[PDB]
Length: 418
Picture 1 (tube, rainbow, N blue to C red):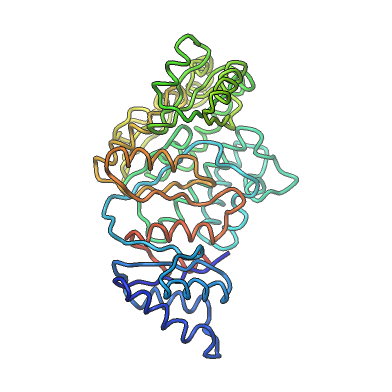
Picture 2 (cartoon, rainbow, N blue to C red; picture 1 turned 120 degrees about the vertical axis):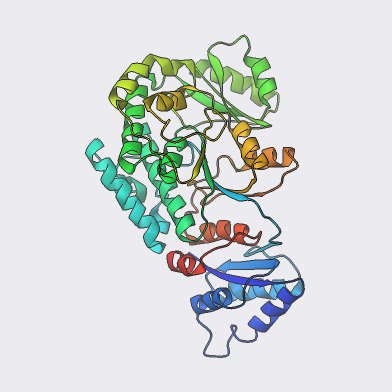
């Protein structure tokens, strides 16, 4: 839990503002209200080209940050920035692996917006599942445990869609969405292409189909450019490139034993790997043994043209929502995800502010390396982290954006943040 105290001005002027602030907040008993201060700092005092945001929950900790701002030193609880970044806004929606117990538990208390979309998502899922999504999202011991795909995929969907809604209600409005694997479904929902129910149905379908492939496959993320990985797996047809998450980030789908040996090899060559939290070989040839159950259970899928842009990690280009028939959805699940390629395009197209709506950052590095490999720096923030899913981590994400020039609706920020 935390409170955002926004401060702004040209250089030195900030140092001043904080200094003056310490004249009243520290005491001037009546000691000023912590939330009452932030709202003022935000409502009053405009917003200039040298910015900073003191994220904390106790008067002591604020004073610390203010003290440091005035002195012209860095502090942890203070996010500083230049506000010199003018590019387009995108929401990134990654896959599984973001999940953790009660991702939703904190932010649900603090934010009405978040809790609402979570409720919507739950209603949507009710007809298709024999368990309580809200219970999972809250960590009810008597509920499923994010150890099964249906539970994971539906929970992550809820989370991402709900974190997206928060970002928006607080004034961060996406000019485009880019999704990765199952994230495309959430991306769609958010762009207006898919409906809550249709998205949910697509997730339930996907999960039925793959139930066969369960434990027969997995995925491994590898800190090597595609080239290297390709050259390591050329003679290994039971492993396949599943994603190019960046110029030095690559995922591989295949049989367990294979993955294990490759990881062994790669751990020995001091290449950093991490096995992915997926129990099947998504974006691999094994996804074709289930094209039927899916294309059958999915049936008709209604996609609508979208108010937001939708860059497909399938194609690698802005796609017309409404072309997202059941085929697109079997393709989503069967095709390498070409993330780097999609982002590279979005960048050349202006997008330079990328927000990852995610219970934990999965693609933040890749976005950065890609943008920095196109001499096109931008702002790349996540939302929550594992074990850190309340206001402080979120407000920090928002802050890192604001400091770099993103507009914001503090009113709504303050509300949902409390």
